[PDB]
Image (tube, rainbow over all chains, first blue to last red; front, top):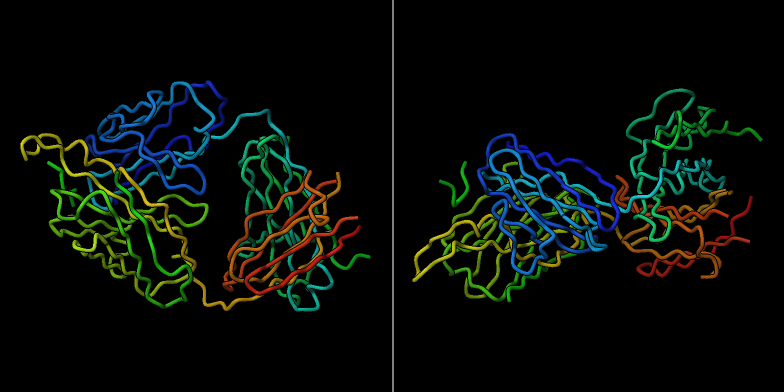
Length: 214
Length: 7
Length: 215
């Protein structure tokens, strides 16, 4: 079906900045497009309807323009409440598509993550499962890539990660990634490595350990 | 198809 | 003032049928051109459109979910119901219902359709978790600027609370949001960068654990 692509997916800014988010549709949607601002734990709030009409009660700093396949939302003077995620929605064709959203967070200087790898506890191993966790602490920007390697084999489909919300004082993010294997598979390998790619790192950092090495 | 208010 | 509110079961098991109700006030589903739609949001993901129903009773569904969705309205009770069949874990998300404006009119005559291009008022949203899991307490394992923490594994349902040194340690503490494992149980880590003891509490199962972690 129709595709709605938002740009950029993520954006850093400071109070007072002028930002512009754009949304491109794969086929023309005339003026049937709406913009919303969503604060965590809250429902999306309507800002602009019909591509450029200012919704009642919405502050003037918000503005929407465009028609057809390219739309843009600009906030002329960013306020603290604007650090949030924005979405565009198309209502010309069914289904009424939403864009992927763009996260607007507090800008700060680049910070590379402090990386740590934790082997599974002997207590967990006795239960038959092995969780290897990798921590990326206090980094910025938010985008980071974690790649697990076991005896040099690139792992896939056996890990899960979650990221904290931006720190109110730090403006940094932290990320935790868990690699899960059966005790049996765990025992069949030696080198467990957590490879991390991030803008603040000249080149990828690898933290690792050899299983059973005592 | 087209939205309820399209055209 | 228009307000909407979703209601239904917070927990549902795979293959089961989920029925969500949207109760509203401030408008009638008998009002010209009005619509009420449903949108969902998996944790950490984007918004996904599900379906919409208008006062003239026209119904439209997401093509990807068409076979599992039924939307209906009860005009006299000011409610819209969405029924989703054979749910699976990927259906856990926060579900929102929302109002869609009809065209502006003058002397009962539509003169502007611009107002229909948006869903102007939303409900707070209702969190629905799909898992075949029964209530269960977490196993707590140690995770040993240095960093250490606790791995709070295999519990259900959310939430669980974690603090360090009985509330005396806060600086450098990061408790990550839990992930729903394919097993249907949650898992989360809580670390701290610097004795250190994590205090874990899962109210649902009445499971409190204090685990001292060292180098």
